[PDB]
Image (cartoon, rainbow over all chains, first blue to last red; front, side):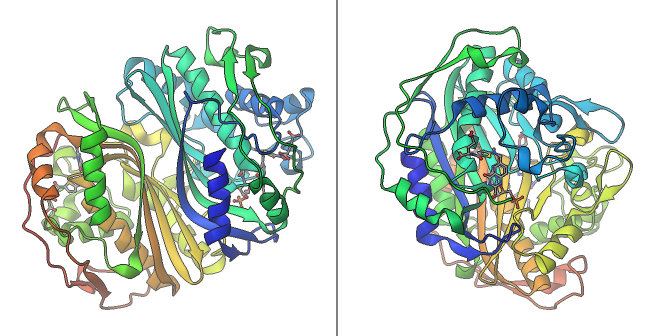
Length: 264
Length: 264
Ligand SMILES: Cc1nc(=O)c2cc(CN(C)c3ccc(C(=O)N[C@@H](CCC(=O)O)C(=O)O)s3)ccc2[nH]1
Ligand SMILES: Cc1nc(=O)c2cc(CN(C)c3ccc(C(=O)N[C@@H](CCC(=O)O)C(=O)O)s3)ccc2[nH]1
Ligand SMILES: *c1cc(=O)[nH]c(=O)n1[C@H]1C[C@H](O)[C@@H](COP(=O)(O)O)O1
Ligand SMILES: *c1cc(=O)[nH]c(=O)n1[C@H]1C[C@H](O)[C@@H](COP(=O)(O)O)O1
C-alpha cells in the first residue's frame, strides 16, 4: 500500500547497515510515523499475498490472555513456533500483559477492559493506553515486545489508535502488525458504537534484514491494488467473544506471495 | 524553532475542541512526530525565553530517583508544586520508575544503569528502552507520566533518542520536555563516548489549552532565531554525578518570556 512501500524505499534510501542480535545484519532507520485512515479500506498489504487467517487467530489469542502456542497449533498457525519452549510457552508476552499485568502489591490489571471502560465512560481521557513493556518480566519473555505500547483517542465519534513499535522487521512482521491493530480498532469501535478513525504507526528501529533485499525490490516493483474491505457479521456481547467466522474480508486481490527467511 | 511553531499552527488549524479533565478545554490533534538533529544546535525554544535552570534541576532530580519536590525547592524550582501532597511527594512518578522500577516479587530494576550498560556493551540492541508507564503504580501517582516511554539507538558512532509523549501541552510543557531529553542525550553520549544524533519526538494527544490562545498568537508572530550550543564543562565519573554547574548554554538569544496560567 502506498505508505508501506514508501517506508521500504525510505529504509533503502537512508538505512544504515547495522549488526543485530540474530547475526543476520539489517539496513536500519530510527524514527518513522505513518497514518492509515481506516475508513478508506482495511490496511492489508496487496503487493504480496498475506494470510489473514494467521493474523486473526493471533489477535484472538492475545485477547484471550494466552501465551502458549497450543491454540495457534489447533488452528494451524505456526508463526510463533521458533521462539516457544519445549512446552509451547513464550513466557509473559503480549496476551498476559494485556489481560493481567502484575502489580507489586499482588493485583493484576486487565488493560483491555480498562481501555474499553475508558472509551465508554471517559473518551476524552489522554491516558487510554495498553502497555506490553513490562520491565520487571522482560527477562521471562521468549522475545521482548516489538509492538510495545499503544494509545486510543476519540474525536468526532471516531476511534483512532497510535502504536509505538520499538523494533520492526519491515518485510515480514510489519504487514501482519498493521493488519492486526486495524482489526483491533474495528472490534473496539464496534463495542463502543464508535466509527473507525486512523491507525497511526510509529517505529523505533525500523529495518530490512540483509537477506530480504531481493524480495524487497521485487515487491517494490508492484503497483498496490485497491484496499480490501472488512465486514464484521456480528456484535458479540464482549470484545473477548469474537471468533474467526465473524470476520469477512471483501475485495482482496493481491500480487503473488513472496517467501523470506525469518531471522531467529 | 521551525518545527515547534509549525506544530503550534497545526493544532490551531486542525485541532478538535475537547472537554479535558481540568475543565479548561483544549484544541487537540492525535499523532505527530518531530525530528531534531542535535548536531545543528541545542533545541531550546528561542521565540520565548525558556528557563534552563528549572529544566536542568528537574532532569537531575529524575536521575537521582527522587519523587519529592524538596530537592527542587532547595534549588528554588517551583514547577511541580501544584501536584505534590502535604509532604511534597508526587508518588512513584518518573524518577522512581527510571531508577527502581518495582518487580512483582519485591526487587527493583534500575533502567538507567541497564541503558548505560547496553550502550557500552551492546549498542546495536533494539531494546534500549526506559519506560515510566508502570501500569501497576499509576493509581499512586499525582499525575500520570506525560513523557511516557523512550528509546535509544546508536548508528555510525551517534546516539539518537525517540520519546513517546502520550499527552502534550504544546505551549507550556513541550519547550521544556524537548530541552530535557536533548540534555539527557548529551549526558548519555558523553558517558558512552558517542556523538549526539537525533532527538525524535512523537506525541499522542497534542493540545493547546483554550486559555493560551493569545500567547500562542503572540508567539506565532516571532521569527525563530539560531539555536544555542550546549557545553558540558566537566566530565563526571558517572551519569549520576552531574551538577547544575557543569552545563553552559551559549548563543542563546531568545525573544522575551511569555507568561501563561497552568491548568491544574
Ligand atoms: C526477526 C523477526 N522478524 C519478525 O517479523 C518476527 C515476527 C514474529 C511473529 N509474527 C507476528 C509473525 C508475522 C509474520 C510471520 C511470518 O512468518 N510470516 C510468513 C507466513 C506465515 C503464514 O503462513 O501465515 C510470511 O508472511 O511469509 S511471523 C516473531 C519474531 C520475529 N522475528
Ligand atoms: C496542564 C499541564 N500542562 C503542563 O505543561 C504541565 C507541566 C508539568 C511540569 N512541567 C514539565 C513544567 C514545565 C514548565 C512549567 C511551567 O509552568 N513553566 C513556566 C514557568 C516556570 C519556569 O520554567 O521557570 C514557563 O515556561 O514560563 S510546569 C506538570 C503539569 C502540567 N500540567
Ligand atoms: C518482533 C515481533 C513482531 O510482532 N513484529 C516484529 O516486527 N518483530 C521483529 C523486530 C525485530 O526484527 C525482531 C525482534 O528482535 P529484537 O528483540 O528487536 O532484537 O522481530
Ligand atoms: C504533563 C507533564 C509534562 O512534563 N508535559 C506535559 O506536556 N504535560 C501536560 C499534558 C497535559 O496537558 C497535562 C497532564 O494531564 P493529563 O494526565 O494528560 O490529563 O500536563
